[PDB]
Image 1 (cartoon, rainbow over the protein chains, first blue to last red):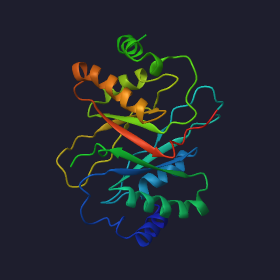
Image 2: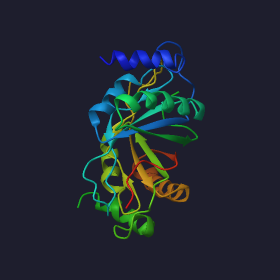
Image 3: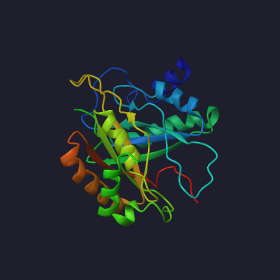
Image 4: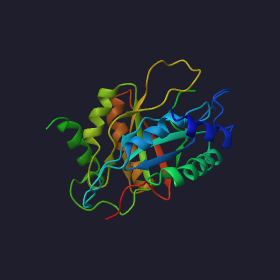
Length: 119
Length: 121
């Protein structure tokens, strides 16, 4: 399921997507991927998983009062070790999506001191 | 309504931040991730940490970290605010309350470059 994207990522970024090896000690960064199409983000939730990248399920952003949004913007977070890895993850995922999922946007995110995942 | 207590607390403690009227900021550059293994508590925070200047997501789950000793899902939500100042304030207020009434809750300052992908008015 999503073999296509999975294999693409494993090839384009073998280290980041090595399903084998050891998680980083802390996840200081992430990429928020957002889109009005939850089905697409769900594809990403399935594909963007490894030892070095952990992704939340798809959820929703809150509506901003005083705008006329016609549609919920969904999102997920993909946690990675640091800023280097986040830049890379965003680059690779979006190169793909640019052709096959243009509804998808990515935003670099950072936590102090790091995201609250166990050690 | 429900959680009237926590709501009133937040608005008295930080009036501008939790003013239910006014104008949202133009961009939300920061947020606080509030997390906990208790989803019911985070549902409370979800209905409560809302205003014109603070917007919170529904409760979701963090992914499990391979090869660790928890076997307990950790839930979270994000509360978006204008910037680092407002995030520091929001975290302080919410956690002063929770420190007494919800010791399971943690707060983490988060920042987005250039800002979080919420629309603009």
